[PDB]
Image (cartoon, rainbow, N blue to C red; front, side, top):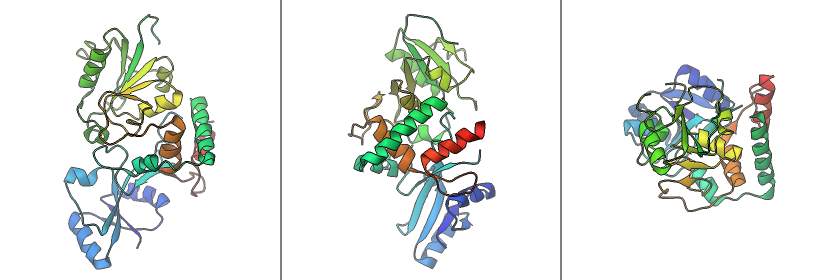
Length: 296
């Protein structure tokens, strides 16, 4: 009777059980959470993303809430998740409230050994992964799905791709702006971007770019690993740490971090990793090795 899930689908419950083998039951309403809590003194609730904030539901302090989300490595370039994020304080894309990732990076107790792995992971990612000929600075803007939670709780001002593309052009009047729209979703876009790169190879649009300008896209964290300068127009999890030139300052972040500190925190300590083959907990490096040995 260790963990409970909040409004998870059956398929999602089985996936979560890989990371939490002690999942016991699925609570389907706030009343069921309150009834079970005073029945057992305290409960551990598994919630997905900003589900509680979207419902404006708050529980007493005896309901320990874990906010779940997909990992970072399963997504950045290289279906059944190999990585899972379990945040007991908040969630990484919510810049309005503290997150456990933010507390890790602030405490920044990173010994010499974990900095080595972070440098190995950076080198590993860069290796496991059209362009206009002009004199202008090449700027790339990855579009997002506007209904995403990272824009709602992670962008303090800009909320649309059009406002992003607008704001990008206002700050860069002469640069060559190419808009890469999000796959999962035109005439007014071209009034601020030069061309619209509708396909060819995401991560291999980064290498042709001089700078990457994003709102809250995880795409910008991949650009940091690739070493390309990135400007943030919102407040993603990698913003505020001086690695990115932030348009709007983060109201709660003062620390200047290195790329290894960011990687060691965001990729190595923050998310969980479970092997796809045997189901055991593995390191972020073994997770990359498994995904790398999966494609060939």
